Length: 174
Ligand SMILES: [Cu+2]
Ligand SMILES: [Cu+2]
Image (tube, rainbow, N blue to C red):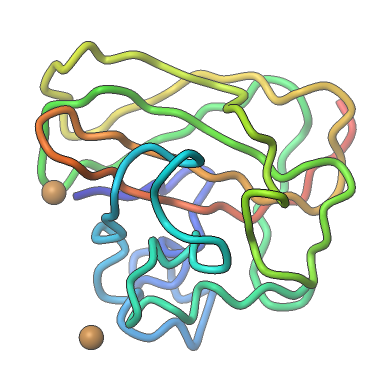
């Protein structure tokens, strides 16, 4: 169980510790650490249209997708660091990050077609137990600007599951 608090994830910003910068999030507000679903996105895992909720019904408020809906973290293109708060540590296969395609539609549901098919950042943890706070250093793909959604995936090595964290960003050109 864990969540990304820098850049603050969509679920994190729903929470009290995110100071409710997103509202009307349902139960997400009270357990942003709990977006657990089958590993293996995009070949498996949460179905299209339910990626942000990790396919969990009572987190479905996160599946709304409009330009106006979500608070966006401002970031500059290039190097980026993601920080996870690991409330319950589990042996870890990897940390990986996907981003929406150039030309995705911010007013349509998040789907595999809306995301690049492969991650832009991948850190192999070789099934080791992580510390309680984890930082992954990454680099954004070239040519990115504007509103984009980043999907953070924390894949658990000793279960069938992973934790899914979408992040809303406004990217300024490098
Ligand atoms: Cu857990
Ligand atoms: Cu419920």
